[PDB]
Each structure stands twice: as structure tokens, then as C-alpha cells.
Length: 115
Image 1: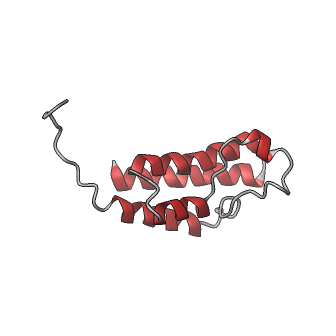
Image 2 (image 1 turned 180 degrees about the vertical axis):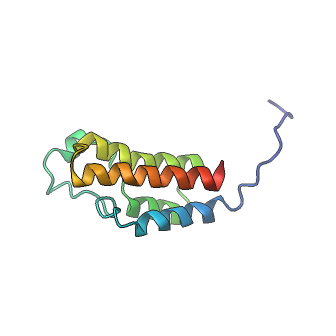
């Protein structure tokens, strides 16, 4: 509350560390469905169904330009990528499996880097 604060966690490396995670997600062999925004002209149903499209290149530009206020807003966008994927793709599909794999890969890096 006013003039009552928990001890100050060092957040000075968070930007660099999110960048490293994101590089590791970019270079994963199963990243290919997620590298670029879904082409809304060429994929019927995407625009109407997926209310907030998100992809790794868009996260990279947001990260690089100071549009994440803290590491939690960064994780919310990464998770959005996988939540969108599950919304649109059957589990038993190459893309559906890719999204589960990448979400797992992310969540472990997230826990190991920050928890």
C-alpha cells in the first residue's frame, strides 16, 4: 500500500532474457506455423474467428520497440499465439501438434529463466 512495499525484484535483465527466449522459439524446427502473421486474405474464417491474431514476428517487433511494459505482458502474447492455434487447428494435424510442442517448449524456458 502507500509507503509499504515488498522487496524490489531485479527486473533489469528481463528485456534481454525475453529476447533470448524468443530467439529460441524462432529457431525451433516446429516454429514455421508461427513465424509470420496468418494471411487474412488467404485463410478463410481466420479474420472473423480469431479476434486477436499474434505471431513471433509481431512479438519480436513489439519487444524491440518497447511495447511490453513488463515480462507478464510478453508471456500473454506468446500464450495467445498457442491459444489461437488451438482455436483454429485440430489437435491431430501438423500445425495442431506444432502448437502443443511449442507451448511446452516455451513454458519450460519461462519457468527455468524466471521461477
